[PDB]
Image (cartoon, coloured by chain):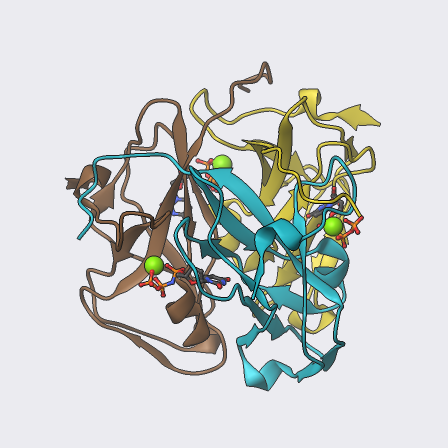
Chain colours: A cyan, B brown, C yellow
Amino acid sequence: KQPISKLTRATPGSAGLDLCSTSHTVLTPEMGPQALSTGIYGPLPPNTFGLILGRSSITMKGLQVYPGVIDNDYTGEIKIMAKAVNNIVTVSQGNRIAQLILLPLIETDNKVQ
Amino acid sequence: KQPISKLTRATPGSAGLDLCSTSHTVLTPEMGPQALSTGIYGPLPPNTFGLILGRSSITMKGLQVYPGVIDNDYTGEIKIMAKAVNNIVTVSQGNRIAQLILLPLIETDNKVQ
Amino acid sequence: KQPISKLTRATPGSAGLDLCSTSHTVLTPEMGPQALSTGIYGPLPPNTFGLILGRSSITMKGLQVYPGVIDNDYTGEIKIMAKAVNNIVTVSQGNRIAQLILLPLIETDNKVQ
Ligand SMILES: O=c1ccn([C@H]2C[C@H](O)[C@@H](COP(=O)(O)NP(=O)(O)OP(=O)(O)O)O2)c(=O)[nH]1
Ligand SMILES: O=c1ccn([C@H]2C[C@H](O)[C@@H](COP(=O)(O)NP(=O)(O)OP(=O)(O)O)O2)c(=O)[nH]1
Ligand SMILES: O=c1ccn([C@H]2C[C@H](O)[C@@H](COP(=O)(O)NP(=O)(O)OP(=O)(O)O)O2)c(=O)[nH]1
Ligand SMILES: [Mg+2]
Ligand SMILES: [Mg+2]
Ligand SMILES: [Mg+2]
């Protein structure tokens, strides 16, 4: 397992930490949502949670990443939920296919139930 | 009407407050976006706004929630904008179908026009 | 080029800064993702990044905006990545078709590589 501290940012001012596919995968529109492996695991830094979002160059190529929430205390593998929009999409091993955004986790008194 | 203070978090470290459907609803891909009732209303805590996002177990089952912005001063009912991706999806009353994330509302000098 | 300081908020408590299409554009579902021009450019205020999200009245009319990340130091034109969901969608010049949300940019020690 690899922690999110192993992820890289494309540039200093990049909001997102890039997530790469660990598998070669072909996706077609009739397959609907697929969960792609990253080999990266939570959890996240204190007082933060994560959002997985598409990379724009990838979205424009017809692979939709559904926005996903990563909980602060998730310790499982971060997966990318993805769907081929219109056409056949081929993901290669190591391709940067999404990005992780870190956001402040606001405390509230909502019941934890 | 029920305020967002009535929502619950799945776990202490869960970023999202779960939103449940108040109706049994069937959705098909040809129907396109539908707005599901929650019986939960704004507004939000001071200096925050909301994002409605999908729950991953729900997205993976073929129901797409379109990300939606909840304004700090919205006092209407929070609705979930949803679409069946490929297949027929049946939502039952009380099913947790999305989640509300709270985020800091940044002040800017943009004209309010 | 116009900076994001030229954007307007619908109301004082609106989280989003509205983005308008500068072109008349027709979109069909078979066209897949299209990048709509706004004539608005980064960069963003210090310590912030942006998210482009749909407006709910627009999403409900069948035009999906794919959530997009605007980096703090992006100096290019902000484009809206959009797709007609089920039907033919006609965007007119000046129509508010998405919104820009500003969010705090969290610093981490991830390699910038
Ligand atoms: O894109 C995603 C979304 C979620 N996840 C993981 C991390 C997150 O903390 C965990 C739970 O996410 P959600 O709350 O969105 N899913 P759901 O509500 O279906 O499961 P749970 O009841 O555990 O909260 O799933 C991913 O790996 N990728
Ligand atoms: O998923 C959503 C998105 C928005 N909303 C409500 C809350 C939000 O404050 C209100 C307005 O949202 P948008 O600005 O996204 N919609 P639009 O720009 O079409 O309407 P307005 O001109 O009032 O801002 O709609 C929901 O209930 N669910
Ligand atoms: O909806 C969007 C998304 C991104 N963008 C622009 C701004 C953002 O800073 C820039 C890069 O975005 P991403 O990182 O999402 N794209 P990608 O990873 O494909 O390109 P790069 O390798 O440059 O980061 O693209 C838009 O104009 N609209
Ligand atoms: Mg990028
Ligand atoms: Mg959950
Ligand atoms: Mg609006």
Position of residue C81 relative to residue C107, above or below, is: below
Q: Which image quadrant: the N terminus of chain B?
A: top left
On screen, residue C62 versus residue C35, left or right, reads left
Taking the view exactly as shown, the residue that stands out farthest to the front is A1
Question: Does residue A95 sit above or below A91 in this rendering?
Answer: above
In this picture, residue C25 sits left or right of residue B71:
right
* Residue placed most toward the observer, A28 or C113: C113
The residue depicted at 50 percent of the width and 66 percent of the height is A77
B97 w.r.t. B72: above or below: below
The picture quadrant where one finds residue C32 is bottom right
Query: In the drawing, does residue A54 fall left or right of residue C61?
Result: right
In the image, residue C106 lies at what x, y percent?
58, 33
Residue C47 percent coordinates (x, y) = 64, 25
- The location of residue C108, given as percent across then percent down, is 62, 37
Q: Quadrant of residue A37?
A: bottom right
Q: Can you say which quadrant of the picture contains the C terminus of chain B?
A: top right
- Name the residue nearer the viewer: A13 or C24: A13
Residue at 65% x, 54% y is: A6
Spot the residue most to the top.
B109
Q: Nearer the viewer, residue B16 or B93?
A: B16
Q: For the point 82% across and 33% down, which residue is it?
A: C75
Q: Looking at the image, can residue C10 be seen?
A: yes
Q: Is residue C60 left or right of residue B39?
A: right
Residue A56 image point, x, y percent:
72, 54
